[PDB]
Length: 53
Length: 395
Image (cartoon, rainbow over all chains, first blue to last red; front, top):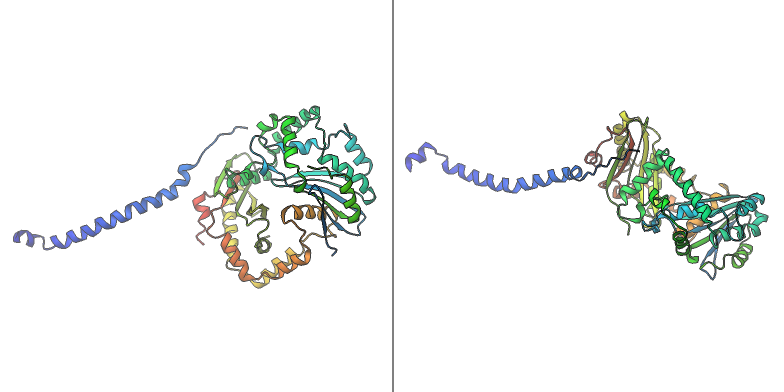
């Protein structure tokens, strides 16, 4: 354990970041997806019709 | 200015008049019946009845109607909108006895000759085949449509060719017998008329008469062979009765690429407030930008001088005896149909002079900013920006 600890004196430090990163990405990915789907809904509902005279 | 005196008869028909010293008169019948009251199975009934209404009534078979109203020397006109129908005549005041009678038969016991029925069907249809030439009307009939979706207001006054071909006397008879009720009718007279004589003539003749939501949207009819592009952008107008309409008219008077007109079309608690402009394709984008800037400009540049300016131009738009009989009648008929009363010009002047810059930018901010627009484009409209872009002035 000690050897491991020394090899990566930051092992603990990091995993806390990674936990904060997972929580922030779980918050931010559906919200950015919802924006994208807002601004892309317009087109995704566009109905085209061909009306030759 | 002489007051507009209103009486009410048995039927419920109102008889409004505004005497003036001009010599001729414009006597008309308004009816609260348009394409908004049609239910997509009779979408051209008002238009086709407006064609059939001058082709003879029992009393005036054949060309009699046109002949007499021609002999008397009067001009016979009719029009139909999405909410109102008007059948008006301008004639020598001494012709009042004649006039009222003729008009009566136009709006009642009108005898639609199926012979004529077929004929008009063809007329309407063929013209429609060419009504496509009126690009502006096209732009304005999809704007209505694109915005007022799933609502009666959408259906155009003309109606779909389909219906035009598929219409019969009985259907017409229905529209006639359904939307021509006496409480929904105004007999308006302007010019050299006496109100008591007109009331007696209305008692003698015509005494027998028996949702909407705005949807942000966009319709881009692309046809690159046309030389010019017409684009209309609108938001939801307050309505006909809403007081803020006046502060919006002043805003339009502030705005006043090419043919950049501005409109405030009002229907019963709804409407379209916006701008229509025709430009070469390459400039469409720029023009769009400009318009948007101006609107936010009202929100930010209501210089008192300009405020006054707009008030003054509005002041010189109000219709009056000077404008003439027809203009006035028309105003009497619309005022009795929409407001239920004739608003005098002094009240209009009071509502204009109470408008200042702060309430103008308040009323504008409520309606232009953060309001999904309805866009209708026709022509070479590839450089016309798409919705996300348009709604996003960002400035």
